[PDB]
Length: 166
Ligand SMILES: Nc1nc2c(ncn2[C@@H]2O[C@H](COP(=O)(O)OP(=O)(O)NP(=O)(O)O)[C@@H](O)[C@H]2O)c(=O)[nH]1
Ligand SMILES: O=C(NC[C@H]1CCCO1)c1cc2ccccc2cc1O
Ligand SMILES: [Mg+2]
Image (cartoon, rainbow, N blue to C red; front, top):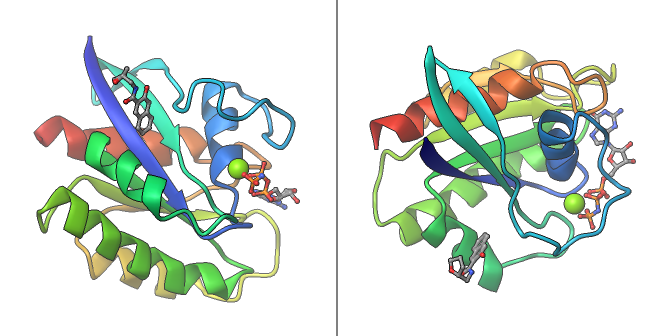
């Protein structure tokens, strides 16, 4: 089985770990022991082919920088998560990607933007802004929610597709 290391990036309150625990543990984060494994693992079939979906979540409310590059340098694809109610996350998506390029030493690398907390109600940045954000990079966009487990699998699965090419 192919091993895919996906580095999940997010602002802070967006809910990066939540999407991971939901896809991997089918549960909501914010109640697990951190630094236990450092990365998540999962076996699924995307695009009709069986591959290993290793979800690697990153820090959100810790201004992680030193380790931030570590995940990228060892990770293949990068899943960006933003909050519809937290416009602050919208600006985070671009600045974060810039960090991926420096470490990845490339331009077009496996990446996927996912609008977390979309099932809430208060969406500051309409889908137009989110969709246009991903288009600016040339990556697919998928709206999902770490609270309803809607699209969580899609967003994560989509990321693998880009990595498979690498
Ligand atoms: N309504 C809603 N709330 C969400 C969603 N995703 C995350 N949250 C909210 O996000 C909060 C948890 O975020 P967070 O502070 O990053 O928790 P953590 O990631 O476990 N800790 P840390 O940030 O230190 O890693 C909770 O208040 C949770 O309810 C979502 O899709 N919908
Ligand atoms: O460097 C790491 N560990 C020491 C050995 C064993 C695995 C490969 O190197 C290691 C680095 C990581 C970097 C980013 C995310 C998860 C990681 C998880 C890891 O286990
Ligand atoms: Mg967390």
